[PDB]
Image (cartoon, rainbow, N blue to C red):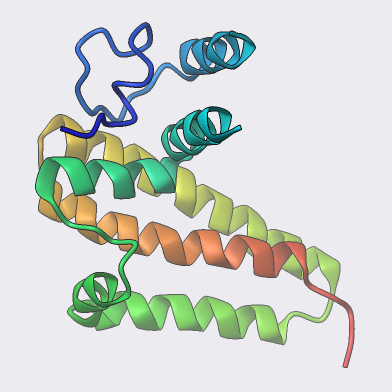
Length: 160
């Protein structure tokens, strides 16, 4: 009965269904227009930010379309658990960042992490087009790990 976030943006989503390929300028224009007409503001704010962000959007879509909520700790853990290869890939980047001695190195890792994210996002695109929810689940947990690294890159400091 409860409206989905896609139902809060009728212009942007005439079909009222969950989709991955959002037209973000239209979302944004509609969001601005809707805000220009406290609780009600913050509820539309949650919704808009969920849809604008690739990670939050994939997590929300999988909740609605496949009923898997990756924002819950144990659901994410059962997915990730199966994938020790991914776990080790991610830890190795954490340890690479630890071994960086200078800004130049750190900005390299960061560039590479940003390319991983737009690559995952493109792959999520193809998953949702082909309705491969299972593949999208794996990529969405992996995406979180790369988003988490983005702030470690931002906050890095030259020292002991």
